[PDB]
Amino acid sequence: MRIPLVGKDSIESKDIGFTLIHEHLRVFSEAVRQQWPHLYNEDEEFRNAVNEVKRAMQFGVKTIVDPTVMGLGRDIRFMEKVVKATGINLVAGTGIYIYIDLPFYFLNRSIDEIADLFIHDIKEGIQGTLNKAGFVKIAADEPGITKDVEKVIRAAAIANKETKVPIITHSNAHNNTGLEQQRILTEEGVDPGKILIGHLGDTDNIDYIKKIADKGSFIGLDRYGLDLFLPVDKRNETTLRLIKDGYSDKIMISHDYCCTIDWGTAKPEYKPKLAPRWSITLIFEDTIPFLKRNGVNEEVIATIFKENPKKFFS
Amino acid sequence: MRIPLVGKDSIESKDIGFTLIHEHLRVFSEAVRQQWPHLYNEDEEFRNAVNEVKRAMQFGVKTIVDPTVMGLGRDIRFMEKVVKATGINLVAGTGIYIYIDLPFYFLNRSIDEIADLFIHDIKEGIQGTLNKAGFVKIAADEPGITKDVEKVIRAAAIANKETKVPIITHSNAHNNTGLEQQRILTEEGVDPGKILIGHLGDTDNIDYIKKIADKGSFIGLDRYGLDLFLPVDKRNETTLRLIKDGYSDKIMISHDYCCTIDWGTAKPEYKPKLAPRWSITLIFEDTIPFLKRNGVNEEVIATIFKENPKKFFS
Ligand SMILES: CCOP(=S)(OCC)Oc1ccc([S@@](C)=O)cc1
Ligand SMILES: CCOP(=S)(OCC)Oc1ccc([S@@](C)=O)cc1
Ligand SMILES: [Co+2]
Ligand SMILES: [Co+2]
Ligand SMILES: [Fe+2]
Ligand SMILES: [Fe+2]
């Protein structure tokens, strides 16, 4: 069969249903959580993940793709507990989340032994369990394409050609990282249709977004609610204009919501100023309503949240 | 009383005895081990640690200060089990080990709350235990003193002024990165007598080593065996010229040995060409004899390995 699910039997990609392609049940810094655990409360972290999933499903969400990996505190056992209490289709991934340099472990190690880490997760299981990864997550940001970042990228390029699984990327919309991720992965033999260049919905600079979509890769309008990168309105006018231009087949929409996140910028007291209406159901309360009283039919909605996720994992 | 011990009552600085000031039982990258535990064998790690500590004790070593902190995989419980197995005096520390940037947890976080962590480990306990940290560890390398690195340094200073525990630093010998650590720490009100600037032993430039010592801080000739930083023989002449010029009042010696280390450079086949003689006992096999073989008497040896550590922690 097609797609691995956490705590469940793998599914035919055709049975994915309404999908949020980019959502985090919980993120934290492994290093920080290992050394200072007094800072965390996994009971509040569970109550939060459950409730945010329990809802969403009430809105008809069938599948959630969670791109929490190394650097973000992936926890297959925690994810597995959420599933028990909600019964959601959850897809976990492999990969490394860095902006500048890889952890020391990787000093003098090759691109391949990084790839073998991803491949291990996709074929054997993740973290001692038999739950396999469904995708590879890689990142790049303000610092640009460093030598270490380029390694994690080329490692993914190998994991894809090996396990066929798709590649999700985190990028900076204002600096070209997204185009570089696509540009490198493609030149390594990866099918553009298997790459989701992420966080492209942070810029209202459409000409750019289009070139990434014109080069065959899915465009991620995936941080709805985080006004600090770009407010809801300018995101909605950006999607819309793209759909109207006939790009609804590359468009993939999500929140990037973290039911719990230890990043300081995310202190439950910068919320009102940085990301006021940010949750895992904001597209149902704003985006979808907005897009339908604006000349976009249920068939296009189905293309974005159903057909596109399916194509991505097929 | 003063100095805290791992799995033991707190001793008085006078009971510290012969001490290896910089040695690691086990180091790994927290994120890597958490996500891919299949790369580690915690049975090998306990056997090597217990072994090396035993041999070091058979030479008369009574106490080992262990500067493994965040970024290097500080594991209090593992340490505590090594103490139970050998009977050693183990000094565990707190702090953050980074070259460039802090974990993502620290975005939009202040120096005070970074310091609050260190103080927590010192006054309350480590990783949920009653074992308390006896010192703070910081770092800087080729990257230099970055905005984030500086934060750790200044946070260390705050913890020091609040607890009185000393500070052990990691430094690059050929870039002044150590001189700056001293600058900043002392400027912030840290008694230079409470600082140990590490890895000065990697350079034969004695003028630089003297300047740091002259300014009232201990000098770390603490990587004996790591031929890739500096061969044993050239380290020997350097530590000799320093002792002859009367600097044993600030000289501290150790190996920075890691009974197990996940860095790709520490792969047991570079050993021959990188650090063949690198052990936790090399200085007994080569260094101490060499000194006697030459000028140094047994009164100087005591001060370097017994009195200096006693000052440091007093
Ligand atoms: C500058 C970082 O912005 P913040 S932490 O802002 C939260 C108010 O937004 C983010 C940042 C990272 C993520 S990822 C870890 O899911 C999700 C949201
Ligand atoms: C052996 C691991 O790396 P190398 S050969 O140096 C490569 C930077 O030596 C080191 C480097 C760093 C350390 S830290 C863990 O005290 C210990 C030994
Ligand atoms: Co991202
Ligand atoms: Co060091
Ligand atoms: Fe994300
Ligand atoms: Fe060290």
Image (cartoon, coloured by chain):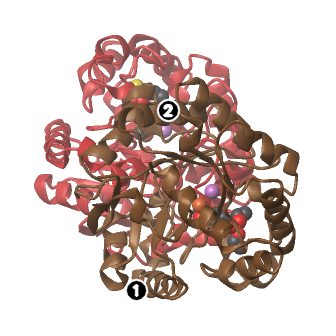
Chain colours: A brown, B red
Q: Is residue B167 left or right of residue B185?
A: left
Q: Is residue B132 placed above or below A241 in the rendered structure?
A: below
Q: Is residue A64 placed above or below A288 in the rendered structure?
A: above
Out of B151 and A142, give the one closest to the viewer: A142
Q: Is residue A48 left or right of residue B79?
A: right
Give the letter of the chain under mark 2.
A
Name the residue beneath numbered marker 1. Answer: A43
Q: Is residue B131 visible?
A: no
Image quadrant of ligand 6 equals: top left
Q: Residues within 10 Å of mark 2 (few under 14, many from 20)?
A: many
Determine whether the beta carbon of the residue marked 2 sits less than 8 angstroms from the nearest atom of ligand 3: no
Indicate the secondary structure of the residue bearing disc 1. Answer: helix
Q: Residues within 10 Å of mark 1 (few under 14, many from 20)?
A: few
* Quadrant position of residue A299: bottom right
Q: Is residue B81 placed above or below A177 in the rendered structure?
A: below
Residue type at mark 2: give it: Ala
Name the residue beneath numbered marker 2. Answer: A157
The answer as to whether the residues below labels 1 and 2 share one chain is yes
Which one is earlier in the sequence, the residue at label 1 or at label 2? 1
CA–CA distance between discs 1 and 2?
A: 37 Å
Out of B158 and A79, give the one closest to the viewer: A79
Q: Is residue B36 visible?
A: yes
Indicate the secondary structure of the residue bearing disc 2. Answer: helix
Q: Is residue B110 left or right of residue B118?
A: right
* Quadrant position of residue A100: top right
Question: Residue at left 49%, top 32%?
Answer: A157
- In x, y percent, where is residue A44? 46, 86
